[PDB]
Amino acid sequence: KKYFEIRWHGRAGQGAKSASQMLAEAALEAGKYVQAFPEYGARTGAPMRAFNRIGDEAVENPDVVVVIDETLLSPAIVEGLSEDGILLVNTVKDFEFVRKKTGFNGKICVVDATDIALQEIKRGIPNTPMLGALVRVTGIVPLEAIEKRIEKMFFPQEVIDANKRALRRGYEEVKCSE
């Protein structure tokens, strides 16, 4: 109840750990209590998890599950996710497909983060648009806080702006089940 919780699923290389860090770093600058760490068992491309706990005045019961590689979708990936919780996915497919793969009745949000990134940052790493999508569907922090963080992690402004556009476009384009 004291912490809002998010559990990420991606494969080594897709940036779940960095995205997780960045979100945490954003909430930290806002004066929030935060925790964030990864959990591996790895090759490069090995499935992994990252976690965030962000105070709101091993994550077995997350408020949101974020799957940045559709390939990892399975009913195990949705363990502990309440019905009033969110399943957020990087996918070009639809809610029905995601529902079939997981068995999650509950809000399912999807966005083609890979393609947003190929367009904006010229890389198929989906983590920044997934962050923007996350901020959009949960409101867990303001988008400006992540942008401020994008500013601090970088480099010429061009590359900074491209990354901020990638965040904004995931924020704008995510679509929801309910």
Image (spheres, helix red, strand yellow):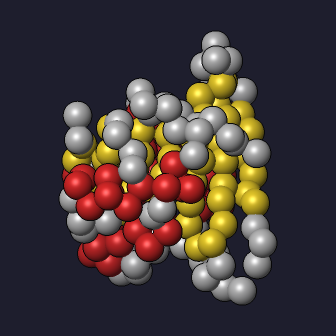
Q: Which residue does the image show at 56% across and 66% down from the upper left?
A: 10
Q: Which residue does the image show at 32% across and 78% down from the upper left?
A: 118
Is residue 133 in view?
no
Q: Which residue does the image show at 49% across and 68% down from the upper left?
A: 72
Q: Quadrant of the N terminus?
A: top right
Q: Residue 153 falls in which quadrant of the image? A: bottom right
Measuring from the top left, give residue 141's x and y in whole percent. 49, 32
Q: Residue furthest top?
A: 57
Horizontal side, residue 139 vs residue 51: left or right? left
Measuring from the top left, give residue 145's x and y in whole percent. 50, 38
Residue 48 lies, with reference to residue 52, above or below; the image says below
**Number of numbered discs present?**
0
Nearer to the camera, 73 or 175? 73
Measuring from the top left, give residue 32's x and y in whole percent. 66, 25
Nearer to the camera, 33 or 92? 92
Is residue 114 in view?
yes
Q: Quadrant of the C terminus?
A: top left
Horizontal side, residue 144 vs residue 150: left or right? left
Q: Residue 89 falls in which quadrant of the image? A: bottom left
Q: Which residue does the image show at 40% across and 68% down from the upper left?
A: 70
Nearer to the camera, 147 or 137? 137
Measuring from the top left, give residue 123's x and y in whole percent. 41, 80
Horizontal side, residue 60 vs residue 91: left or right? right
Residue 158 lies, with reference to residue 94, above or below; the image says below
Q: Residue furthest bottom?
A: 43
Nearer to the camera, 159 or 99? 99
